Length: 14
Length: 303
Ligand SMILES: *C(O)c1ccccc1N
Ligand SMILES: [Ag+]
Ligand SMILES: [Ca+2]
Ligand SMILES: [Ca+2]
Ligand SMILES: [Cl-]
Ligand SMILES: [Cl-]
Ligand SMILES: [Cl-]
Image 1 (cartoon, each protein chain N blue to C red):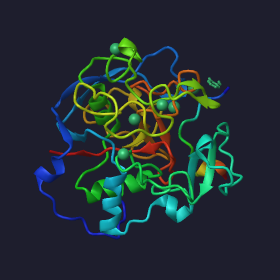
Image 2 (cartoon, rainbow over the protein chains, first blue to last red):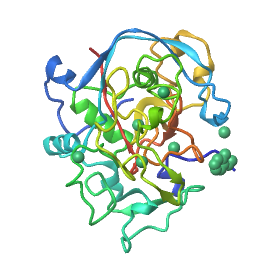
Image 3 (cartoon, protein in one colour):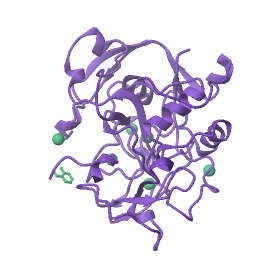
């Protein structure tokens, strides 16, 4: 639905 | 980039540095991709001719055994250890392992696991006793640069990575050609089955494989496609390389500023039905102190 995610970032969980 | 280290850089000879590396001669290649299904936000295009100065590149991603020797010699503490957690794929978290409630938006298969780090890749209770020759994982971009500098090396640029990974083929889809499993043989460690629910392990592995698994490419590099994502030196952008200039076409270094660093090559989790990012032109990024169970690196060096 949005661009697939392969690189999970520490910033993304905040 | 100007890193800070708490260990001295040891003296090493050219012969020592070059062990396990292949010499890529200076020359040109066609970088990028124009697959019509590429995600526009990834900036795989345009295809362009890039000239590179000669360089050395590791045949293998850096292994657990090698990273352990670096840590033993320096006392280096990885970003995941400082933070106290790293990202583990959900299917690899042992039941009962303490986990954070953290959510990676759009990617619920990633679990933030306290105590997951390079030596305990699934969290407390796991180890690398049976994975000495697997790629080191849970290493951030900072950790990779620290290792590479200690080793007398550096990270490859995205262009260096891609020239080496293409292995002398002009605009092929994969390091070895255009078919994913030529002659019915698996050539890389990616996902088979139904992502993210069930990995059939048809290629032999439902996690990382040894760094020397599968046939190499035409230049002698192993697992440039699949296995683990590999950090490169460049800051990420989708469009810096769309400009036609010496800076973007001769030894290109990427944009001078950014928020995330480039990662190349795909991993054991990639699949055509979701990311399709195990093609050699594919690219993504991650922020430089981030770490995960499917991300490692290989080094490059100036001859
Ligand atoms: C959404 O656009 C989406 C979701 C999963 C896999 C691919 C894509 N494009
Ligand atoms: Ag992927
Ligand atoms: Ca696999
Ligand atoms: Ca790879
Ligand atoms: Cl997109
Ligand atoms: Cl091993
Ligand atoms: Cl082929």
